[PDB]
Image (cartoon, rainbow, N blue to C red):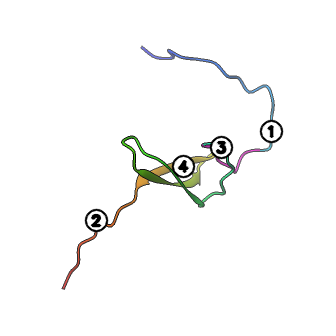
Amino acid sequence: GSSGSSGGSGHFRCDSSRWCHDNGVNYKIGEKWDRQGENGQMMSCTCLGNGKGEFKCDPHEATCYDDG
């Protein structure tokens, strides 16, 4: 099915339209911060916006081979 969980309306109308929130921190569209991963390593997130303040996170590593 769908609509299983529910809770948390929007009574107030703050001025947060171009900001993001993860661990109680205001990030600017494009900015980047550090966080924890599913396993344990650290993950880097980059604020995108596309609305309220969407964002993504990808694992950083030096898995780049050399050419020549």
Q: Amino acid at mark 1?
A: Cys
Residues at circles 4 and 1 in contact by the CB criterion of under 8 Å: no
Report which residue position mark 1 lands on: 14
Residues at circles 1 and 2 in contact by the CB criterion of under 8 Å: no
In the rendered structure, find residue 52 and report the number of the disc placed on it. 3
Q: Which residues are magenta?
A: 16-22
Label 1, label 2: how far apart the Cα atoms are: 42 Å
User: Image quadrant for the C terminus?
Assistant: bottom left
Q: Amino acid at mark 4?
A: Phe
In the rendered structure, find residue 50 and report the number of the disc placed on it. none
Report which residue position mark 4 lands on: 55
Residue drawn at x 54%, y 17% as measured from the top left:
5
Report which residue position mark 2 lands on: 63
> Which numbered disc flags the more N-terminal residue, 4 or 2?
4
Picture coordinates of residue 3, whole percent (x, y): 51, 17
Classify residue 24 by image quadrant: top right
Label 3, label 4: how far apart the Cα atoms are: 10 Å
Q: Amino acid at mark 2?
A: Thr
Mark in the foreground, 4 or 2: 2
Mark in the foreground, 3 or 4: 4
> Is 23 situated left or right of 5 in this image?
right
> Label 3: few (<14), some or many (≥20) within 10 Å?
few
Classify residue 33 by image quadrant: bottom right
Label 3, label 2: how far apart the Cα atoms are: 33 Å
Q: Nearer the viewer, residue 22 or 36?
A: 36
Label 3, label 1: how far apart the Cα atoms are: 11 Å
> Which numbered disc flags the more N-terminal residue, 1 or 2?
1
At numbered mark 1, what does the secondary structure look like: helix, strand or loop?
loop
In this rendering, is residue 7 above or below 36? above
